[PDB]
Every structure is written in structure tokens, then in C-alpha cells.
Image 1: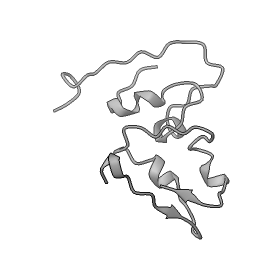
Image 2: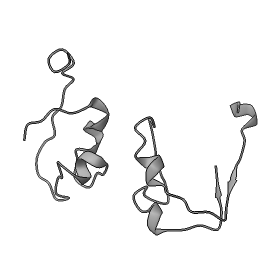
Image 3: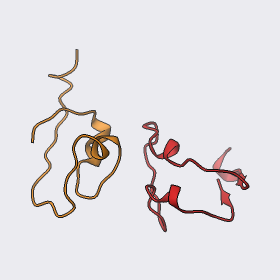
Length: 50
Length: 47
């Protein structure tokens, strides 16, 4: 989408293999704030919004 | 310690950093005393 009109995808009722994201060398940044990207597989959420 | 690497992965060569080269084959200690020195070698190591 255009940044004036961004799209939000709800992620729910599923298993998230976050290392598939973090290991992807295409990503120019992967800055994480209240969590460290290494910890995400040990940890879980009510929903995730992309 | 001497080695060649892809320029993307220089970021992982530090105390407490992570990703495949630091996870597997060159791990620094978290209490490291030292310097990490790197430069582009595309003029030498590419063909």
C-alpha cells in the first residue's frame, strides 16, 4: 500500500516461526523495541498486527 | 583474528550480537576487550 493509506493485517490463531523473517538477508533493518528478535519463538501474543 | 566475510554480516561481529556467523563459526564473548576492524575487499577477494 501507499503510506497515506497503509493496510493492517491481523494475525491470529496460528504458529509464528519468526526466525524465517529474522534470518532473511533481504531485510535492511529488523529493529525490535519491547522484545529482542531472538526471544520471539519462546514468547506469545493475543494477536499480532502487520 | 583474520577472516573474510560478506559486507552485510560485519554488524554481527560484536559482543552479544546474533545471526548465523556469530551463532556458528565466530563467537565473541559478552565481556570482550578488543577492537573489531573491517574494510571492503571487492578489489582483492572478488573474481
